[PDB]
Amino acid sequence: GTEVVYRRPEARDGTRVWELIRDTGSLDLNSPYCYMLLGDYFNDTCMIAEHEGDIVGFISAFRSPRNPETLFVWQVAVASSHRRQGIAKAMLTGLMNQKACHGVRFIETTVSPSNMASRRLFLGYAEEKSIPSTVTVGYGAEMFPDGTTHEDEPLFVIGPFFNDIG
Amino acid sequence: GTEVVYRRPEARDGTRVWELIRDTGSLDLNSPYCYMLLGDYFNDTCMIAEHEGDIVGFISAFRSPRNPETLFVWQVAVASSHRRQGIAKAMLTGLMNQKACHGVRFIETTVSPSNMASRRLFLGYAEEKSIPSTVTVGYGAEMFPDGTTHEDEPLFVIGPFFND
Ligand SMILES: CC(C)(COP(=O)(O)OP(=O)(O)OC[C@H]1O[C@@H](n2cnc3c(N)ncnc32)[C@H](O)[C@@H]1OP(=O)(O)O)[C@@H](O)C(=O)NCCC(=O)NCCS
Ligand SMILES: CC(C)(COP(=O)(O)OP(=O)(O)OC[C@H]1O[C@@H](n2cnc3c(N)ncnc32)[C@H](O)[C@@H]1OP(=O)(O)O)[C@@H](O)C(=O)NCCC(=O)NCCS
Ligand SMILES: NCC[C@H](N)C(=O)O
Ligand SMILES: NCC[C@H](N)C(=O)O
Ligand SMILES: [Mg+2]
């Protein structure tokens, strides 16, 4: 085998990341331009996984502007062909080592009910680090547009990763 | 008639903002969830305009994480009903005068060449302030997906606003 390689995205990755997100089904697809922005302005806090030249994983995240100790994790995707190999866990652990994630004391993310593997990713991460997790309302189904059905997006708060140091 | 009123967005505005952008038929439409995140996490650098209870304008923007003296302006939309009344100018100048924009020295934004009104919004902002504008390559058409056809998105850099 050929090991999966991990790196930050670039603007040029935007199309291929877009294609990865669209091919999941279970994520809400943003514009290609959005993923170029993430690769450009936000790439210090995002991650790509590649295998034999193909993008097989992506995480988008950003530090909250008002609450910078919080990293919001937006989308996590691994290509169908490459699931259950530890790529998402490796991307999340690797994201949290990045220089721009120094000092992050909480992760926030929303995980619906049908994103069952995603729930195990995030709650398993908290377990393995022996860190608390809590779930609040997040964005309910009612907030979404009329005339299609979206699941609730409850908010997971994972942390604190480290103590308040006097 | 009734004055347009301006405010920061909130997460709950995400659907209505999505619908405004959709209805333009001419902006890259993101997910409804994206606009909820903008209203939640980025609201200090965004804005809404409303008239008689309807959302008629939106800007999204954020300060660049690496280069926080730069405000990136992502999307600007005004409902077709309400165009050419100065709502976009009012949203932009209002935005730049908000607390969260103190210390911004540059605006960055992309403006495709057929978007004549957007070009005028940004270049007119620079011109009224007597501040430089510069255009560089941005995101060319070739970056966008196969089988779709997108205009180039050249990058406008407006500034510096001041020289401290
Ligand atoms: C969430 C997602 C990114 C996980 O990526 P991944 O690389 O396969 O995940 P990993 O291999 O790193 O596994 C992370 C955790 O979830 C668990 N897990 C992942 N996929 C699972 C599955 N299908 N069944 C059971 N457990 C699973 C792993 O066992 C691991 O938990 P553990 O730490 O208790 O060992 C991936 O499933 C994805 O993109 N899914 C979208 C499709 C989808 O879930 N659709 C649901 C609607 S049909
Ligand atoms: C770009 C947009 C936000 C401008 O909003 P607006 O509220 O109508 O703009 P304002 O009234 O504040 O005017 C801003 C500048 O644009 C000019 N302008 C706006 N619409 C114009 C048009 N149809 N004709 C020529 N000038 C135009 C104004 O004269 C003003 O320039 P000035 O300062 O030289 O006088 C709006 O056209 C819009 O939402 N368009 C749809 C979204 C988009 O950009 N789609 C892609 C393009 S087809
Ligand atoms: N965590 C995922 C949240 C939302 N469903 C999205 O795809 O952006
Ligand atoms: N400035 C607009 C850039 C892009 N066309 C979008 O709609 O996001
Ligand atoms: Mg142009």
Image (spheres, coloured by chain):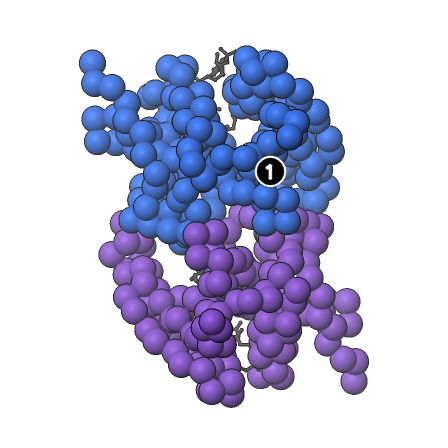
Chain colours: A purple, B blue
Say which chain tag 1 marks.
Answer: B
Q: Tell me which amino acid carries mark 1.
A: Thr
Query: Eyeballing the image, is B139 above or below A118?
Result: above
Depth check: A104 or B60 in front?
A: A104
Q: Quadrant of residue A115?
A: bottom left
Depth check: A135 or A57 in front?
A: A135
Depth check: A125 or A49 in front?
A: A125
Q: Quadrant of residue B52?
A: top left
Q: Position of residue A139 (x, y in %)?
A: 31, 60
Residue B159 in view: yes
**As drawn, is B80 to the left or to the right of A101?**
left
Local SS, label 1: strand
**As drawn, is A154 to the left or to the right of A108?**
left
Q: Position of residue B21 (x, y in %)?
A: 42, 37
- The residue beneath circle 1 is B70
Q: Position of residue A65 (x, y in %)?
A: 47, 51
Q: Residue extending furthest front? A: A166
Q: Position of residue B94 (x, y in %)?
A: 41, 27
